[PDB]
Length: 169
Length: 171
Ligand SMILES: [Cl-]
Ligand SMILES: [Cl-]
Ligand SMILES: [Cl-]
Ligand code: NA
Image (cartoon, rainbow over all chains, first blue to last red; front, side):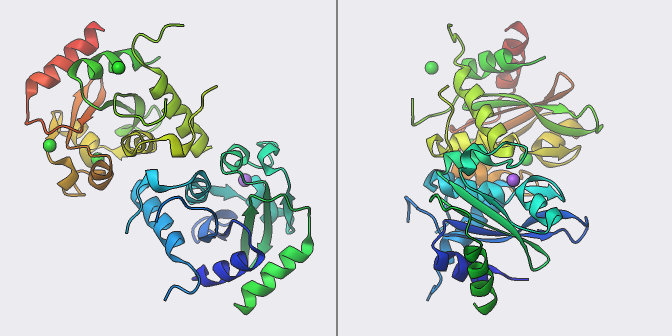
């Protein structure tokens, strides 16, 4: 699809730090890759109703590193978490996105920064980005991930609220 | 084992910004991958470390964390350090880019104004531009490819390649 506006409305509404849609590979069944995202976090360096520009710029920088443009020194540590997630690919069963696809239900990580590296492969990247809460759930034939620098106890109403905001955007 | 001390002596001696040894994949004939490097460029942060290996070891540690005691965070790096770090991800087919070109041709490729090089010759010309790297040189060496680059404009000088190989083997 193109999911950019849906991701933006839903992340900005719940006021979390970022969202990613992990989509199933066209070529490799049961392999998740980066589909699209929205970055809603802090920046240190500077009609777009939904503030898509910084997300489009982080994407452009990722594409140039992986072979008003941003340079690497412009990013916060939270922006680097967002950008390096674009490189990640998950086998069904693998990590929190692969886990959520296989299990067919949410994985809600509180204290994500301390999660076992075999449950959450990104726990140390989360720690450097001050990301505390990370949530993955099956949605639209892929996996929707949201994370925040805030500590939020497991609340299935947040997931319901994102799916609804997403589908009505 | 490793080339870290050899790379350090030779890059620090010629006073260039960095060196990389691209080594042929054990698994894939004619594919180059990152073997080892030495970063000799600017920084913005701050047992005897004679050759200043620590920052190179820290840039490697940060790369391994990004690809899944004084560890670096991404915000700590200069734009030249980012060139050095993202090179660790790159893989080249024989014939492909300047390292693959150097392996295939069996001789040096000396890029001046590397920031303006055609992207089919030098895949990294825009990364070079963001890192203020002007001169990039690859040549076959030890069954792989040695790459050196600098923020300076240095016209083609095969005596630089001779001095690096000699410094490298006498290190
Ligand atoms: Cl020094
Ligand atoms: Cl290249
Ligand atoms: Cl030059
Ligand atoms: Na994970």
